[PDB]
Image (cartoon, coloured by chain):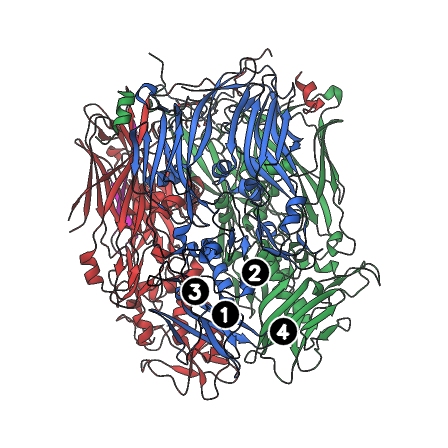
Chain colours: A green, B red, C blue
Amino acid sequence: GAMNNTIINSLISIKRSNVFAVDSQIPTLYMPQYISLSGVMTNDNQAIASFEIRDQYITALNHLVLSLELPEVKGMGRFGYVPYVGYKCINHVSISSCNGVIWEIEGEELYNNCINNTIALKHSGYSSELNDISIGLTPNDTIKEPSTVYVYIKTPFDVEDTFSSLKLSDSKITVTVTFNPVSDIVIRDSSFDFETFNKEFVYVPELSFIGYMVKNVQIKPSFIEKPRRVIGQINQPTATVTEVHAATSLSVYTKPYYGNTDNKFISYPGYSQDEKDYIDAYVSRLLDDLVIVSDGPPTGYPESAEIVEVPEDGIVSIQDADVYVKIDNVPDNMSVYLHTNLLMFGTRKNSFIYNISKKFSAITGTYSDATKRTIFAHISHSINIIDTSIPVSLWTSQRNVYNGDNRSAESKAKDLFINDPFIKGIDFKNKTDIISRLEVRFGNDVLYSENGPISRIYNELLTKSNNGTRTLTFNFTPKIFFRPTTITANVSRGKDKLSVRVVYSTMDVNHPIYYVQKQLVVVCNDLYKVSYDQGVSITKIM
Amino acid sequence: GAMNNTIINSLIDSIKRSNVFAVDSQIPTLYMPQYISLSGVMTNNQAIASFEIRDQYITALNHLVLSLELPEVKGMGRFGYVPYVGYKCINHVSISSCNGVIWEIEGEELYNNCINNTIALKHSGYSSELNDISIGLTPNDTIKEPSTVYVYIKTPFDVEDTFSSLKLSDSKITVTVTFNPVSDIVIRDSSFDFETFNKEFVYVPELSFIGYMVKNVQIKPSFIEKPRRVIGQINQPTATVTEVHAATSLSVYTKPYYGNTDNKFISYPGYSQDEKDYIDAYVSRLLDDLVIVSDGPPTGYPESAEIVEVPEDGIVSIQDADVYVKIDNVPDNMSVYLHTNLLMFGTRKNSFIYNISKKFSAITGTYSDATKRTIFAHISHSINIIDTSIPVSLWTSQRNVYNGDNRSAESKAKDLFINDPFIKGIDFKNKTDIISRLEVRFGNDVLYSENGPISRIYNELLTKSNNGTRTLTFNFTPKIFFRPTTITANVSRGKDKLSVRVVYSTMDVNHPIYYVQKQLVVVCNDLYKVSYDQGVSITKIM
Amino acid sequence: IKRSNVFAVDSQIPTLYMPQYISLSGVMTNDNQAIASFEIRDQYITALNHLVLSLELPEVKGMGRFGYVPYVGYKCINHVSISSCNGVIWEIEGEELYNNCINNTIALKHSGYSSELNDISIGLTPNDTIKEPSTVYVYIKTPFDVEDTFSSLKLSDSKITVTVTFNPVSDIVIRDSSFDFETFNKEFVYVPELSFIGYMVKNVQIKPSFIEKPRRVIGQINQPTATVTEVHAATSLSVYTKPYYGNTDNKFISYPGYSQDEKDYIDAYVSRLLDDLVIVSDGPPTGYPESAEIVEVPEDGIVSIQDADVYVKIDNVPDNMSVYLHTNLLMFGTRKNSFIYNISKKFSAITGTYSDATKRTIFAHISHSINIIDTSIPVSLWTSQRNVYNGDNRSAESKAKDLFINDPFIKGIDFKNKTDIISRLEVRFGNDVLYSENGPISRIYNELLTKSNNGTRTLTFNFTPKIFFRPTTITANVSRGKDKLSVRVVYSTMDVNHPIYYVQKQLVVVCNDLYKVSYDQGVSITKIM
Ligand SMILES: CO[C@H]1/C=C/O[C@@]2(C)Oc3c(C)c(O)c4c(O)c(c5c(nc6cc(C)ccn65)c4c3C2=O)NC(=O)/C(C)=C\C=C\[C@H](C)[C@H](O)[C@@H](C)[C@@H](O)[C@@H](C)[C@H](OC(C)=O)[C@@H]1C
């Protein structure tokens, strides 16, 4: 009939496993409930939220979600939230019992664990409404409407759902959330009254979790991976994690330190977070001053600026670099001018110069008589992600022989303070790999060494993530159903620590990014045993 | 050698260890799969397709895929299919045996179950060829070329492939598919001859499934989740699901009711389905009438229209709202005009007014002498997804004291009839969350209550979906291999019904969306036991 | 009542092991095809999985247009073979490895998918840098990765040799005539390094496993049949089409670069044609063949090319100049009294503004009917013997901008594999019809079951969980002649006056044969029969 004759003839003693039917096992009798709790706020006057979970009927819990009520932002100036605002709010999270800390994570590490989860990232705050830079005109004008963001606190209790869930029978569980200053989660200009905003802003958190009421629970001991972070000394290529006895993994990455700067940047693309989006935003900001259509030489620029009239030929020569500038519908009384030194950096008076005007090759557009502006059609340039990641301070630094920032006062007023706590590398997109070589030593012996980021490639492949780190995985054994595979220590032979040594690729000293400080971050996942005898407790595997 | 000495020494016995590097290859049940396609029996007012599966060699089946041959669309006017046309075709699907209905789903619920599946959605019809609004010029001009769409009928028999598959214990399985009217799956204008199209259109279905010929099948009873929806009365914040005895989940969402309207809308973005795409399409449609370049006052607009000449400063004042309009290359004989009341709403003669022209702040462009039209460069506006989702009827409703629709006859002729059966909320993107509070009661007692959509956040996280609903999950136990965890009823205490009560957000009476009728939809997944003794049969768990 | 514990689990003690990421430099050998050999012999390397081949791409200096094919790393691979002293354990053809990784976005990005690598860069001076040196990572997906440590290739004190055969550099490069490929081909050398996750296992308990080995068969040019012989235990059978560009110079009018969407391919083509399609000139335009029919646009704006009307309106046109439309830019016809495929007719509206400063036409909006097929027509077919007309009426400037595309993994008849050219599929086991279809329902099931947007007409026989079970296979009957799989397709009929009708097709049939992995006295595989 419907089945082909060749198949029916091929089919129509050996022990065979049933693949078409299964005995439906009766599970443990339980009832789940989505429980939300309001916390206790406390105040370096850091904001701390405490959530106490104690209920006879709450037998187990998993899937922690922290909601945050972002207030209405009213006033004058430019304002916007950092992408994934909710995760950036978190400085530290700790789940503890009467016997102490059961599990804890640093804000950045929780974000790193959720970077592959698109849904969790969108929930935490990723919209044009939240992340684009909105402007307030009147002192009562609404810049940002109030919104609620949801931060998924990924814990090891979620790995195998009910099986991995944190059991809390006859024990009090306290979820403590430490918040980063509101400065970190906000991108604003000088016009914005941050002083008042910081005073008026208050974190409004509410912890939600999936609670389980289990009838006659059969609690058995489990294993947990607890992350440990070590941040090296400023620009130092070495960091050491002490007392390493049973580690499942070791992650190594770099972070920029903007202490020597005012955290002000020329441009920000807002919601659009692609590398091209960052570059286009920068080009757009520079173009206002780069090509000027004026009646006689342009005014409102520093004496230091070298604004040159574009010849009939269209080509302007800034040293070896040629810039083709051709604007249409230019009035008979006006000429086309090019700012030949918009941003320039040099450590010596007659040496190499890093000039941003030289990074442009062709600028075409049409002058609008109605709006008295220049509408740019096509731009041919060599601007990179690093250029957009240079803090304004480094252009006007003492290392610079030249003035540095030759932009108009109008353009300089549009600069934005960016204090994102989770920036990696030396650029906003973490594009540039500054680690030339990695060395990992377990005790005094070399555990691993690499010249290329092959550990990052394996991390990206194995975790199915596009934003991985140089990670050394020691556990390839299935989680929850097995005791994780760990590096075994030998205290007697001094093999009880992990020492990381990197070799940073050095930059040109005449390039402003050379002066961006670096920090080596080393993350270690230590193995602990969860014991439930007389309350919940953890014990370090040694 | 290749392995580091520190590792070699660390390893080079007493404890019992599970083999993680090898496994005993289990011999499976002897079977042979086959992709079987069947032509059905068409019945009619609603189109019904019946597919009879009766074969001794077809032991089990799963993965139902319904194919649909869409005809060539010839004639005059604007025409396009709704996105994911194939799913929108479906009104109801039912898999039944001689012992009755085994499993059934409402068209919208099948779509909601597949909303996270990008592949299944693309297969059902998501292309510029199908969804963009094409125009026919001559009565024989081809608007749409014939195409075939594939609708994946996701059933509980697919969860664990061969293990979950529907077994055919020498029984006749009848797959019944009820189709929605062709009006629902089509977006057209007044120019399109729908009358003839509706008469000429016929659903051409073909049911495909993966059939399995199993040698010596060992059938065991299984469990199934059957969905049951309840739609509450027009503009009512309550709905009750009766005879709830064993439920695995409960979903709650809103649907708009467009009965009081002609289902006509000003704009549609076509294939491009982003929120910005919907907004841009609307702005584009309004701009034709909003800014006019004419020799003297513009003509072809109602007497009710207040078209004002743009002054030398460029700013036009519509009450408190200021509109900056500056067009380049305007001929000496012509002037720039702004329609100050393109679309307006009001309930009283001298109260608040919702004017779409006020929603604009800046309009810049250049007049093209060659095409005699205005090419808009940049638009600064406050137009939202709700504005685009307002049916034209509401602008010209009796409630409105003003005329309402002050557009040109040209613009009004371009309006499109949208009858998508799966619209949620009050806008085309289901952006606006109109549920301010949710209350779910099991009898007299409150089972669950929320002020924020935390149940929607959990649904989105747990299902890895970007388009979730406020869902209460009671079953966190692995499917197929276990009896699902259900909310247990108490008939004696009157706890055998689920009552849902919402608190809708209060809107302004001078805003046309206030008059968009709402309907509360509550979906319940009831647990049933699949019995194979003397044919396939289902029994409600009570 | 007896209940299964769903809230707790006995944490099983695993096999004592220690993993290590091991990288190895190979031995290069030279139809003078480049071959890299990697010898893995270590007493302490007990097992291995997750093979990643790194490639150091050199600095490209010189003149002309140059760019790498998307996912350059995968396209470099012609064949990969993992073998022991007992012979080949597992092997795959370059295209099949790519097809197995097409659903993996991460692996694809690693192999080379960037604006830096895939956009078409231009070199102006003989020392100008076209492309900066870069390193690409190719994930060699093997059956040893399916269940991580459980599926891993065990090395029972045996020598494992990973052999990688490389495709010519011509395949992975998109270049113009201006680019000195002759010198580039001589100077280019593949620089590979094989990485894998090695495992040192204390007291390993090796048990025999099962492996699926892919076998492809390519049919003769324009033959709708292909047969896979000695089929005894197959888990799946994939059927697809590949274009053959032997009868062409592999030159194409346009390429979109990094932007790989269907619209991106179309927009790139429209952009290339627009330079010649609408001309603003002082008197009739020059520099075009005599065959070209460039017509002046009337005051009305509408130009009539037969039944097709083209609205052309350019702003700020000088008083001494007029707007001209090329009414036959690219045309094809088999007879002088037949239907004509004219690319100029595929346009309905062209609007723009003439820039006096740059002496150029800046196009604002284009209304056209150009498709993915149009963008996939090799230039050779426009100037084909079958065409009674000239064919390519473009300027010499436009013709010089054409790019040589030799991507080895092109499927169907278009660059996006959009057009389905199989009207009917017939699969025969022996001489009896095993499966037959009129629609690509096997492709729909493949796309659904594998969660891939780029599937093939695949017949899956194994729906049993991998590694933990012996795979379900189509059982053969040699006595009844049922020991071969014969595929017969019916190609979808195309119009003879459309240039794409002349694209030579090749039927590709892939069979996954079941083998048993034996570890007694070294690693060995045995074909299940
Ligand atoms: C969701 O499907 C599950 C099925 C449960 O019901 C049973 C009765 O049917 C099985 C089928 C059909 C199987 O193929 C296996 C299986 O291959 C199996 C299993 C199973 N149960 C196990 C329990 C433990 C403690 C360890 C290993 N286990 C197992 C089970 C069952 O327990 N595992 C093994 O045989 C081997 C050799 C190794 C380890 C495999 C890891 C531990 C699993 O893949 C694990 C991560 C997990 O996915 C599974 C244990 C699954 O269980 C859960 C809760 O996730 C099962 C595949």
Residue C399 sits above or below residue C490 on the image: below
Of badges 4 and 3, the one in the foreground is 4
Q: CA distance from mark 1 to mark 3?
A: 21 Å
Using the image as rendered, state which of residue B149 and residue C368 is in the foreground: C368
Residue B341 sits above or below residue C76 on the image: below
Do tag 2 and tag 4 residues touch (Cβ < 8 Å)? no
| Start-end of magenta stretch | B218-243
Q: Is residue B124 left or right of residue C271?
A: left
Circle 4 residues within 10 Å: few <14, some 14–19, many ≥20 = many
Do tag 4 and tag 3 residues touch (Cβ < 8 Å)? no
Do tag 3 and tag 2 residues touch (Cβ < 8 Å)? no
**Is residue B219 rendered magenta in the image?**
yes
Q: CA distance from mark 1 to mark 4?
A: 17 Å
Q: Which residue is disc 4 drawn over?
A: A326
Circle 2 residues within 10 Å: few <14, some 14–19, many ≥20 = few
Q: CA distance from mark 4 to mark 3?
A: 31 Å
Mark sitting earlier along the chain (1/2): 1
Q: Which residue is disc 3 drawn over?
A: B280
Q: Which residue is disc 1 drawn over?
A: C363
> Mark 3: is the Cβ under 8 angstroms from ligand 1?
no
Quarter holding the N terminus of chain B?
top right
Q: Secondary structure at mark 4?
A: strand
The quarter of the image that holds ligand 1 is top left
Residue A73: percent from left, percent from top:
54, 61
Circle 3 residues within 10 Å: few <14, some 14–19, many ≥20 = many
Q: Secondary structure at mark 2?
A: helix
Chain on which label 1 sits:
C
Q: Quadrant of residue C424?
A: top left
Q: Which residue is disc 2 drawn over?
A: C400
Label 4 amino acid? Lys
